[PDB]
Length: 4
Length: 202
Image (cartoon, rainbow over all chains, first blue to last red; front, top):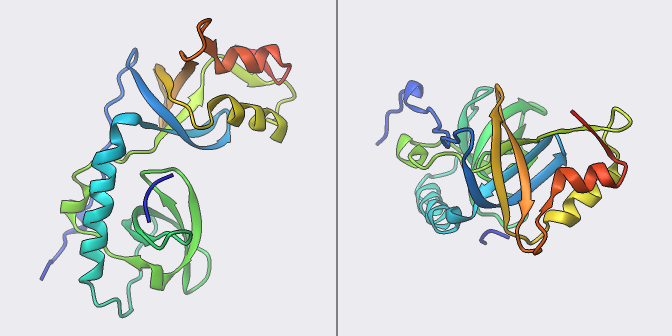
C-alpha cells in the first residue's frame, strides 16, 4: 500500500 | 547547516518481548523463515515520517558526491512511487548504484546514487518499522521452501490483519506465530503449511  | 556525527545515526528497534502479541500486517515475504511484519498501529506514525522525509529531502540541493558506507542508514527514493523512505545501504552494485533495504517495509532494490540523500538523527527517532520474522515450529519439508509454499503463505496473510505472537528472540529476528483470528476457528499459518505438506514440525 503506502503513499505516493 | 547540519554537521552529523555518524555515531548519532543509530537506528532504533521495536522492543518486541517474548509473549508480545500485536495486530499487524505481513508486509514482505522471502520465505517462511525470512519475512517482515509491521504493526498495524504504524500507519499514521509512518505516513508522518514519510511526510517529514519528503519535506527534508526537498531542501537538499541534490547535487552529487554522496557515497554512503556499507551499513549506513540514509534516504532512498523508491522507484515505484518516487517517495523518500529510510534505507540501509547493503552493498554497492556498481560505482554509481547501491543495493538498499527499506528498513520500514522490508523490501529492497538497486538504485542510482542520484536516488539517495543523507539522513539526519531527527529522522531516526521513529523505530524501524519492518519487523524481521521467522515462522515458529516449521521447517521446509524438502529442506528448501518451494515458491508454492511461499505462494500459499502469501495467500493466507494477504490484505489481512494478523495476530503476530513472539515465541522467541533470535540474533537478528523474531520467531513468531501468525494467527488469523478473522476465522471463527483460529488458523495458524504454521499449521496450514504442515497440513498442506510443505512444512514439517520442530
